[PDB]
Length: 291
Ligand SMILES: COC(=O)C[C@H]1C(=O)NCCN1C(C)=O
Image 1 (cartoon, rainbow, N blue to C red):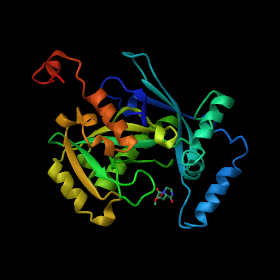
Image 2: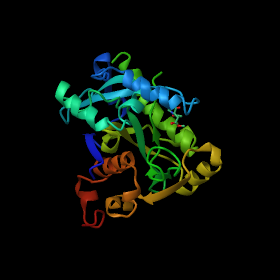
Image 3: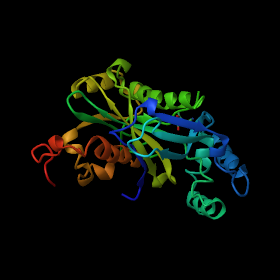
């Protein structure tokens, strides 16, 4: 799977909000481009002069994420975050010359990402009361990953002493994206756990935080809520469910070739952090079949 790399695998079956610190600092921003940010400005002008209804929006930038020594007390994760924008993304990660910007970042800064926007995405492994995960089909008419399978998520827009509010907006935004797209009531959803962070090598290495969320509704009820919004209530074109039993071997299925990279990230982390039991009971052959 060359189009996805794991930046972080969380311990203890995943991390709650209260165990994560953020450092939001202009030291974590993209570096100005070697020939000037006029190259980003030019791509944006060309785009607005064809699609003048487009808008810029701020985004969180992932710099890095440091896990504490395992088994320790206190905060378990430090997220180093900067700020970027939709416009900076279109002029860097989405650019035809994105591989050249990575090589120049290696040369100039010892960092393949130094000249990349790298907006932080969020995604969920969303489980039902009857032990299915939730999948969405993308429109064949959109620019990114057309007609591919996805999981719920988005790219949160901004607004440890502003740090804790930033972690709160990240956990909040994954629930909000589930309510907006799947049309589920907020009170049917668990507090999320962070499973890890995955990078999309097809989009020049931009990262998504992958979460586990439990719903108290069955798969038949989740479908009813999704469909009852109508075609205008969602960006996706369909919803479907795979038993948690069968997610274990999903990378061996024909479905795998149709999954967008960030959804592959979510399923790998679900299998490693929520699947893959460590104890004698769940590890017994009748409950963990070999092969
Ligand atoms: C229609 O989808 C797009 O690509 C539009 C785009 C935009 O205009 N501004 C920021 C990101 N975005 C949205 C709606 O989130």
